[PDB]
Image (cartoon, rainbow, N blue to C red; front, side, top):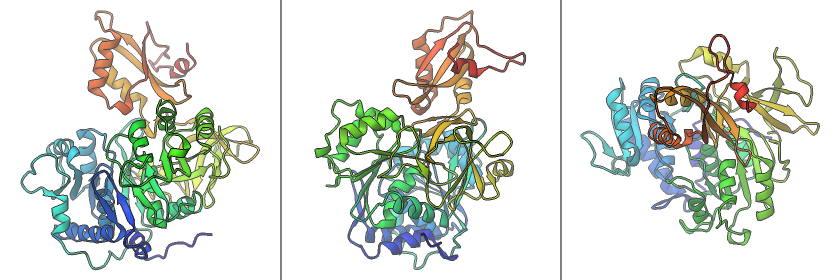
Length: 518
Ligand SMILES: O=C(O)c1ccco1
């Protein structure tokens, strides 16, 4: 039902051309600024020019480390328009994480929000990078020699006259994806990939349209967010609301109620964690206060009671689907008019789904298998990692690392992960990372972290800690340490002190016994 993109294709030019019908409609609006489609176009093309003027060439990478706001799609589309590959990254990571991404991407320039300039600085100082220029959006401190203010940079250059003559299957952008051990993998996406997600899911599954106002709690750096709040709305001419701050129930409700930009969102997107938090909130708005027509969920399985509670309150379902960084967006989903809570719905038309057992063979309905996806938006490889590329991308099929069960009605029910990671509110969290942080406290002897469901059925990490006999470590002291050592998104929901952990003769911790509540 969807025509493939032409083999000569630049995604940025495609989204700009789509919206030349509507120059004066708002494209993006945030707390302090707004861009119409024609202003976005101009700024996008001037940034493309600016990047070429400082010597960044076609196929070279730039790091895009930016809070959600109107400069973000300018950054992203401007690079793409130039045939430069933006590497769009999480804004909550450490200087060490970024130092690795600068070296691994060989980024030649960085586009960074002033609030993130201190962490970027640390990463630049410590690494062997190739960064020729730092372009700072909304600087929060004085610019260092050679750094340039984003607005000045865009404003200094005339718009690039034509886009880079890219192929549809040329790399257009990277995201990073983390595993339970080891450094993040550079997921390489082509120009065609987000065309396929925006058409097969944004348009043909959600039925987004021009008069929509989109608002995603999931940031633009998330694959989920990048669809929800950039590629999908730009595909149909919707207006997008962007928000720089942390998405709490209050910040979201403020927006829902038309507190920014004079717009009320019609389409909202977020993790089940956020929806649970909102429904808990004593000032949840009533349906007559909001203009929501469509509530999308992804980033962990949606507990049935959260959808049911949302539906009872709003008269609107939560439409929960699953995608990945490697598949770019959702491939298995409930539909806006067909929702079965306790399942992730049906394959998205355009994607083929398989469940494979221990030998790669078929599994009987109602038995769990590992999920593999065949669809036209899959990443081509992990950059510079052939072993991991071979394990994940196998002849047109992409291994998700999830397990699922197929139901008699052809829907799919989540069954666990194949690789120890915990999916906590949209972000993959490694139990092994948390264990290695806890053992650096002198009062901890050993530590084990597993996922446990909270009162809402949502998975959070839980730490089992053996304290070191000669020391005094209290629960609070450990919480103080965790607070200093880890990002809030990685916190254990609770920590239990035990006398010993169950292990094999080799010292392998039997984490499955801790999940069983021994
Ligand atoms: O379920 C996810 O985590 C997802 C949705 C779209 C992209 O990633």
